[PDB]
Amino acid sequence: AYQQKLLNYFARNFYNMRMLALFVAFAINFILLFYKVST
Amino acid sequence: LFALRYNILTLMRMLSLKSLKKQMKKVKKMTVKDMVTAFFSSYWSIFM
Image: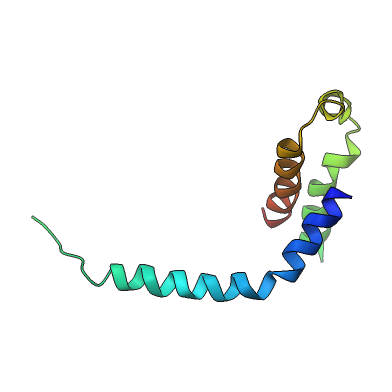
């Protein structure tokens, strides 16, 4: 039953996590724009 | 097809070993935390 609950939760929230991954990727790549090479 | 067959057989040898008894000894004594961990580990093994 708890396995099925986890299955249902992930199936319900599949798309929202796909959106969140893109948002987090844009945040990480925005942070990487301030990146400086050193001697 | 040979790669599919071989890799899936390697994955399912997990179940085929029948040595799951020593895990089940503590499956009697899992918590919800542990069963969630096993749930995640199954998909991790599939992805591997």
